[PDB]
Length: 164
Length: 164
Image (cartoon, rainbow over all chains, first blue to last red; front, side, top):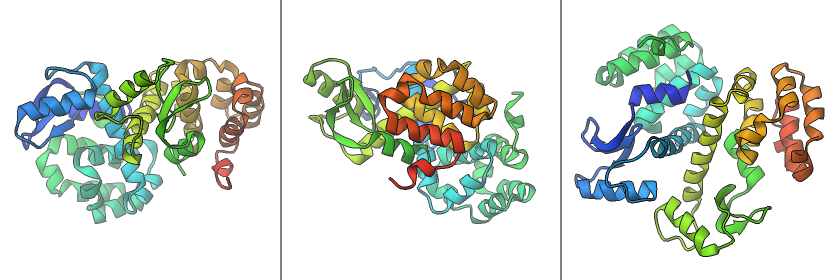
């Protein structure tokens, strides 16, 4: 278990253009193509992203390539963020992944917004952070994934991904 | 200082197609475009990867998208490699970056062939590893960069990147 396997789980893998929850066009492992409602524009964005005319369908390897861009971009923006960075650098390897997971899902901006849970994490107050995180709109919106992310922060283990 | 800042120094950032050492067309931060002697070929690879007609020049942001791709690809490849993985998992965060740096530079296969220096690192035999690594053709080919990566494995500090 690592961040790659962990997001693949939380995000899944689709090789055809699909609509996420707010219904925008998406492919691979949670890779947003466009906010434009035109599926002709999503198919042209996609051909652009992948470097070939795909006719709406990609391979596993092409999806993993977008995924590598997205995860490292996630990590890079954590490191360039005044607020996320000292938390991330304080965290152990498993817990860093939990943090990467949240940034991947909701962006560096909304993760930098968790002022008090971030402080609890920075102070190593795992149980308080876990409780505080559970109260968020984020949790209330995707409670299955959030609870799995919060168990990772709480325990520093890969338990919430074992069985499944 | 992290793996991103460390490979930026090590590889530099070139926004225009250049020729690397085995004289292969390259752009961004050590991004290999092609092994065609042709330039319009390398220009057509670049266009494909970036998604616009570049005519051999890119932005910082474009170079960083490719860089993000290459780094996480380097990490995923460590994690999928039966010899690199347990070494990587055993290493602290600084020295992990040293291993990522090697893999970024010469690929997963050629790093997985450092049989005996890999084993020394897994056993925390830092000086012994540092000494063995300095005897490599790799070190002989790019000694400045190699010595800096070997200092990081050795000390697990960022000393070799501090005063450059």
